[PDB]
Every structure is written in structure tokens, then in C-alpha cells.
Length: 67
Image (cartoon, rainbow, N blue to C red; front, side, top):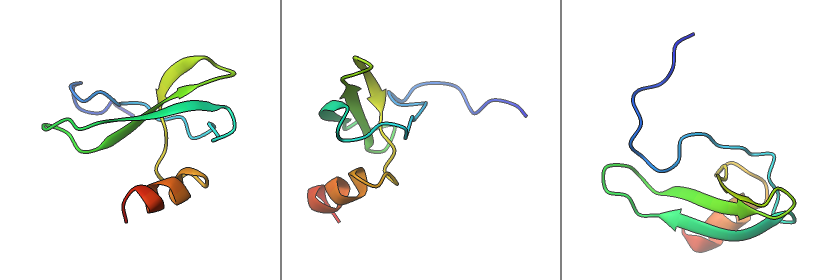
């Protein structure tokens, strides 16, 4: 299979393996050309990533942040 369109948005690859436990802090980018892509920063991994919105722990977070 081929690759998605070009690259512009901040988030591109999402790793749902993350969990609020190993998550350090949450962050979001209000990019105009793109939608609201929720970013984050892992602990045990020590790095910034893009968390999945369908996550089990983020589903509660996203529900409180805005529903």
C-alpha cells in the first residue's frame, strides 16, 4: 500500500500504546490548516507523541475537555 498525502500538520503518527500512567503531560496544537491534533509527552519513553482520541483513558479526558 502507498503512503498518505504530504506532510504539514504537527501530528502524523499516533501511538495508542500510551497510557495516562506513563504519560508525562498533555499538549494540543490549534493548527488552522489542520484539525485539533492532541499531542503528548511520555515518561518511561521520555518523548513527545500524538495520543489516540479513541484511547480508554483519553476518552474520559477528551470527554471532560470537550464533548
